[PDB]
Image (cartoon, rainbow, N blue to C red; front, side, top):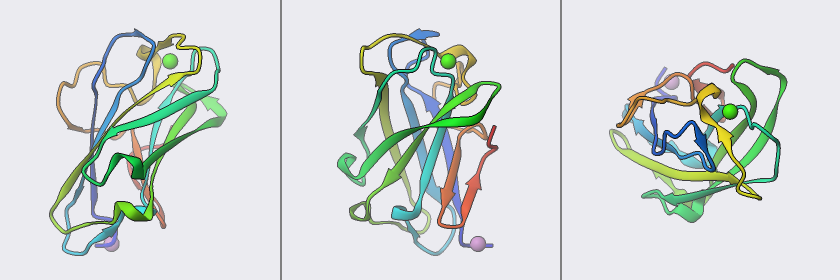
Length: 153
Ligand SMILES: [Ca+2]
Ligand code: NI
């Protein structure tokens, strides 16, 4: 009612269909009056891997400190349209809190261990058009309560 006032905006920094990396950019805004503990916030980006390989996420920049933002990869089960995996982004306790009426960006990249290609065009979360942050319901966010933003595939 006031405990999940996290607005999520998104765009892709690189929008090549055949791409050796995926470039998720999130902007998270606390739209309410109470602080949000980032350690409990998770984000998902859903995609089809187009050849499974070890993958790595890097956070290149966030005001909370990029080393405090990490990513892991999980398989969808069952797979569905546009989604056989998701990236899950998490924040450490050192990321701190997101104050009332403030926002942070989370900018990063992921790639396969052998740098082989993805097809971005079929990915559930991919936005082929946005060049700026946009309120995007095809990425999801979570608190300790579970889902707080978006539509899971
Ligand atoms: Ca794909
Ligand atoms: Ni609430």
